[PDB]
Image (tube, rainbow over all chains, first blue to last red; front, side):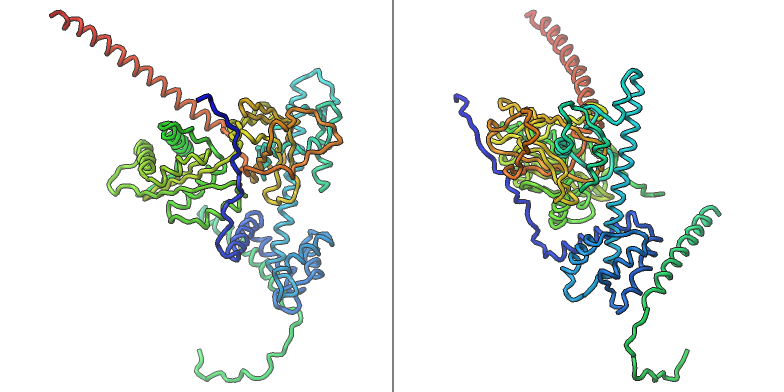
Length: 202
Length: 48
Length: 305
């Protein structure tokens, strides 16, 4: 007896069974998920149209394009890519394409899919800002004697619950850094305009 | 009639999808090229 | 359709199914001095996935680890699977659904490997996944060992989060609360240390108060970190703005996808079920009370000899 302690440490081992399958199967499965999420938002018409900017630039007819050809395709699809980002992506693509001096017709599909995912996340962010401002204005209207200066400024307790709605979840422990990054000036009131400015800076 | 009309509107939409496919089809053979040269004569007279 | 209509499972019904599976495992644990297994949302999700797959397929581990990589699992997790058909001449409705799930739970109760694993003192977190088809039902479990356990996740205000969790490791305290992008782990999402964490060493319960607004709320997971010496952890200390916490010295424990824990539907349904339970039980206790009263009335007459 005597309630003998005791402080003991249970080793939390990250031993989550690294796959025994050949890595090629895993990469194929990730490619399949990429195709799935591409067809998710990519309609059959856009899927049937984007190829209108790969083949002819692919002059040698072996289903590849280099940086210049890929950038020409991207400008021909009406959506542009950064020079350094394009170089980064193309070299990453070539890492697994030792025998091909270019990217396949599916490479442009994947590039456009990732670009569209990023952009759509951006429009979702913008729509969320608009909706949050609408809700804040409605709540202010709920109080007809509060200064309009708070329009765009929100409390500590009205700045926490909005990451359980849509898109790509931020969980509990995904709600602490940006407060430090914004650094409220010892006032516990936060401007969502600052969030608008800082979210896209990365 | 309504079911068939929905199906034929889908037919028109997929026809335009195929037209975009063809647009991407006129895009594959710009210059090349390498001279499939010598001989393909033999066409045995047994025909269709 | 005409002959065999679709058997679309009741979301409420399956939620009760898994809740009662957890409660039954908790009772089995309590039978012999064992703590009830708590609810792990990540293991619950993975078990639901594997149960859905199993119902028309066989026990497959490659899919298990592929889902692990997809959700970025943290900690060792041990899996349990059973696929039991339906009796060829057994009638099927909701009541038979409930009874069949209880019978499958018992079948789990008669497996020595399953009884050991799902009751092994090593681990302290349990998750259940159930699925079924025209023929068979699959029941699957995920057991995980973690230092910090999740106990409550609610919506206090319009824009306030409120999640409470009890520390299961005495020597580890919640010092790091940070997470990396599930889609792009390299991108610093969000996190802070003890300046907004309320930890009680005596109880090992830690609560989180922070700020968070509406951006991209569907498809990523948590990153629960822990550090040695909670006593060395400066809880609720307003640190100077020129200092940043060092999370590299902090060890991650539990990468969990985020969902309502408990979901208002889940907790409300559990509340209704339990409350009806006590109502019927009080009627029952009245039944045997009056029974004893009248039995003693008869015994007083029989005591006339």
